[PDB]
Image (tube, coloured by chain):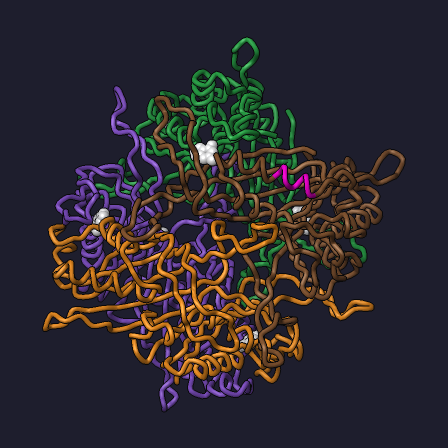
Chain colours: A purple, B green, C brown, D orange
Amino acid sequence: VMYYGKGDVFAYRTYLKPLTGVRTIPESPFSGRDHILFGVNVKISVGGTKLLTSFTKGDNSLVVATDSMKNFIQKHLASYTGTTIEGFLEYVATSFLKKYSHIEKISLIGEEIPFETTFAVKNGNRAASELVFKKSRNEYATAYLNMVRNEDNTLNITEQQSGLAGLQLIKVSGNSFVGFIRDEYTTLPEDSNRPLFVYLNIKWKYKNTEDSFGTNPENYVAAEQIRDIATSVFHETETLSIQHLIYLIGRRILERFPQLQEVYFESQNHTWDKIVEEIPESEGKVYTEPRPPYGFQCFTVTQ
Amino acid sequence: VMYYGKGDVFAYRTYLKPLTGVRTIPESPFSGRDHILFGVNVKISVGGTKLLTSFTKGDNSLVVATDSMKNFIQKHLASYTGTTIEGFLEYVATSFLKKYSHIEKISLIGEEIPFETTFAVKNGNRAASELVFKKSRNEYATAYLNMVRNEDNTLNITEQQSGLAGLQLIKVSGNSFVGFIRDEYTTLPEDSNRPLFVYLNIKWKYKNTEDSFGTNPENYVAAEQIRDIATSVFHETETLSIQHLIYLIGRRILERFPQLQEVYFESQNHTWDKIVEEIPESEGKVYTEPRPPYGFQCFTVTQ
Amino acid sequence: VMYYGKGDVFAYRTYLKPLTGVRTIPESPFSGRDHILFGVNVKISVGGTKLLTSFTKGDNSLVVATDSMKNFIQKHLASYTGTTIEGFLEYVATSFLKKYSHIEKISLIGEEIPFETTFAVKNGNRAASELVFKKSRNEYATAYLNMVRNEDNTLNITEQQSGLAGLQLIKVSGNSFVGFIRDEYTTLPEDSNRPLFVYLNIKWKYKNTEDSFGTNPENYVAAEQIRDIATSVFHETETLSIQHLIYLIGRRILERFPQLQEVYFESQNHTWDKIVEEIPESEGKVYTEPRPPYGFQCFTVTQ
Amino acid sequence: VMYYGKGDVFAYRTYLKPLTGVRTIPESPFSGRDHILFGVNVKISVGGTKLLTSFTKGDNSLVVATDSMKNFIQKHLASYTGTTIEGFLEYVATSFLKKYSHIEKISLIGEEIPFETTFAVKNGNRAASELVFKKSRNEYATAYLNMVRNEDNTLNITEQQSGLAGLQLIKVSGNSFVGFIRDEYTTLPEDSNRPLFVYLNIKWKYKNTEDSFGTNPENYVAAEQIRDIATSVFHETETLSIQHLIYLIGRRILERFPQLQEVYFESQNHTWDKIVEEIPESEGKVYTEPRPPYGFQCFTVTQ
Ligand SMILES: O=c1[nH]c(=O)c2nn[nH]c2[nH]1
Ligand SMILES: O=c1[nH]c(=O)c2nn[nH]c2[nH]1
Ligand SMILES: O=c1[nH]c(=O)c2nn[nH]c2[nH]1
Ligand SMILES: O=c1[nH]c(=O)c2nn[nH]c2[nH]1
Ligand code: NA
Ligand code: NA
């Protein structure tokens, strides 16, 4: 392995071109993005056989300083005329390979820094502010891209993936986990009705890489829509396990977006422990945080 | 100083009595809380001169185990019939002093563990789910209470405070910071138009402690309303400093809630650094994260 | 309340004046600090009636910019000729009040950013490197200082406190917790031999502020020496509770350092849960991490 | 992808069999581990075609509960008679595949939870306590192991890797970074003498998996010895870049440990910003923390 790059390249852009013209789905009212505030955290990795002596001999002649990679990314966010993170990564990658002939491969990760609408009273009525935004530490969109230069100096995207990260959902009832293996290692009781709490990281790949850029937005798959499918399916489903649930979520995603080739899930179980089961004259209970061990699942659904 | 207690007592309650009957204000559509899911993190501190030998001699005869304090809190959330965190703390404090005669003082902190509505398709239409909630890591309500036992075994609340924590707001334009001291220690340029980014912690005290419990909800001051005043005022104001802004927020809060005696602010400046000032044929710019040092302000406004 | 300031002011000085000649105690080898690398995280808060209109009217004419206070601190670290954080704080406080006549009160917190020696083979043998150091995320020394300007234009230190933070100690054997109250809320089983795991924050005050500065190192009390008393006493003691343990640590501290007026403890309990009680052909046991709730104690020993 | 498992499985064993007789190297004093306290954080992932219907149909009949895998790990730590994390992983892997015939693949990650000796005055003199230990949040050893069940029912280790994580090293002098590309994106000034601050994660593979277990300690490569080579080499070297530095560390590692097949580096640059270039009557300088973006390097040296 041989590569280097820059991490935590935060870049905030105002008044990016709005994303509109999206194709709707029943599970989501998502209709586009205003892009008054566009925040991204970018990681960049570059490689190439001509970097060897930078390691083996301390020769920096062909080293793009990582500081300069940060400048490159931030400058390109100012000139970017597109409407998605996926498109932004493509802009950066193509530009970077055309600038630096000795680099054979670039890998980029972009993670949305999300903001939420706030409201203000003005002109006699309360309405959404165009100036004040609330920084969110909840779920966010993600994007991944790998580009390579060939022997004839053409460039090819070799892998692309989009995603939604940091989704934390609890369903208070309508979940079971029964029937699992009961042997000398089992102390977990069967539960007919648990408050399943799951962390979801969902990633998806397109059949055609161009649909990820948003140039023809009707073919774009928004993380917001994926979020809304996941919450809807979790609601609709009498879950039998987290495994059971994410398969059904993946199925719904690929049904809604026939342009997707696959969807990949990384889930974690953070369900609370029960303390009070019976509350007189009430259907409530009390739960508390569990010990640190968490179950997890990794699963791909293919079109 | 001599006291002990328990921290990070997480307790999640389902179907608490809903909060309704709230008095509205122009800045906020807040109309109550469903309380399908009610989450609280509780810290408890207890003291009393009869605890001395537990320290000076290792005599545990009068020590309520901190583990038992956790049990006490969680059990009392199951039996609590009220509608606010402030009321919950009062329930716990009064119960605890009546149980343990040798304790002269209790101090409690409760921090909301907030959840957000999600949506699902069912019965032919998309609607808010009554079962699936999204865990939020953004702002949350808080409450503080101190109770003491007197020589005649009566109990008195000696201090109460409510608050909103974790509010992070950025205003992209309409802020200035000019006119400050320029001497041999000043290298900060004057800025006519900056994207002020502030962290706000806002606490408020009532003129009458009973108005904090929500038993007569019309007198309750909801953290949600405070949130909405802060976002509205930040929007409305051509800010001259963070000091300038939080004074105006405090003023609006005390005008809206004449039952409040004071409001206290802890603010932090996390404004981004400018990278790209001019973008051809566009009013956008690019900013990035600053170095770690942050300015802060602490300020009380009184009625 | 009315004040403002700067936090997370990191400053790293190389080749500070070494601290030498500190009187040793039998529990600790500590005699001084080489100060090849001296790292500190400072928080500064300033107050004054003349700051009012900075809040009420947005008048910045008497606002030292928080950015300037960061410059003030970092420049003063470069010009400090002393040998302790406590003395640095006094240097900064005195210089700042002398510079800015409109300030009536300055409060400073300094936290060491600690580093540890590493091995290097020098003349064919391993030695402590004078060049390479390891950044530690374990315990660190702290200092706190308040200074005011009086009616007659004199300056006076109103409060000074040194400390040790982040000490995490576990004693595998020789700890009991028994004899505590058993009633309807008690589920904690008595334990005659538990692996007590405590977090410790220890703060001490001097009889004479002068001694905090280290100008006469014979009277200086180093955090490193406090660390070593705490670990020796915890080893020596069959603890009966954390309460019992910290009282004994405090007594020893005050015996060794008669110039100290008091020692303050903030302790947390993080003892693991036992999973395996007895292992064949061994004295060993297996434990795991507990649920989040943690006990805590706070207690002051006076000379 | 299809697998599932348990993470953050903390397990603390007292009085594990000591590791003794490890062949020493001149850069490190390390000869073994007392194992009075042996702490590990395990992550387990299992796969198998027979798990499909657990996802597609919600059939739990062939689901080992993740909670049971936690029990499996913690019980096996109690019965492990070996002396290394690498050997523990093999013990667990082999036992788990033998127990559950429907599993085709197990992957294990083990991370040391490190502890450090403390001082106690025993017979009138300070010594390392056999009872009291300090929890460290600095560097720690790691291990990784994949095992499969073949067609003919035999088990085979498909991958094994040991490592060291969380090493943070700063060298105050003797580091340059010069001669890198200067073009329209370059703003980083050349530096002939910088206080290079690097984060290091080092992972190594053995020529013979057998050597990882420590059954014959003469062939075991301890993370502690890797730590000491890294610090010695960093001291010895006038570094020309982090790239240059890690290549040299790798070469030394492989020279000292000829049984190793390769060494892999993941390095980050966290060098401070300089604030004061020259201080009168001293060789010292002042620095502060940089903006968030950090450089990183990844490189593999082979035997
Ligand atoms: O949904 C679940 N899947 C699992 O594999 C599991 N194991 N314990 N609990 C569980 N819940
Ligand atoms: O609003 C502000 N208040 C301040 O005190 C300050 N100091 N630097 N920038 C600042 N901004
Ligand atoms: O040392 C302890 N003190 C306490 O007060 C306590 N309560 N639970 N466990 C405890 N251990
Ligand atoms: O050692 C370094 N390598 C790099 O690639 C680099 N880029 N900026 N600074 C750097 N330092
Ligand atoms: Na729209
Ligand atoms: Na309503």
Majority secondary structure in the magenta region: helix
Q: Along the line of sight, which residue is nearer the eye, B151 or A244?
A: B151
Toward which corner of the image does residue D198 lie, by quadrant?
bottom right
Q: Is residue C159 above or below residue D124?
A: above
If the image is split into quadrants, where does the C terminus of chain B sit?
top right
Q: Is residue B14 above or below residue D72?
A: above
| Residue bounds of the magenta highlight | C250-256
Q: Along the line of sight, which residue is nearer the eye, B191 or A69?
A: A69
Q: Is residue B94 left or right of residue D234?
A: left
Q: Is residue D183 visible?
A: no
* Residue C176 spot, x, y in % from top left: 44, 36
* Residue B255 spot, x, y in % from top left: 59, 26
Q: Is residue A63 above or below residue B78?
A: below
If the image is split into quadrants, where does the N terminus of chain B sit?
top right
Name the residue: 49% across, 43% down: C198
Q: Residue furthest right?
A: C152
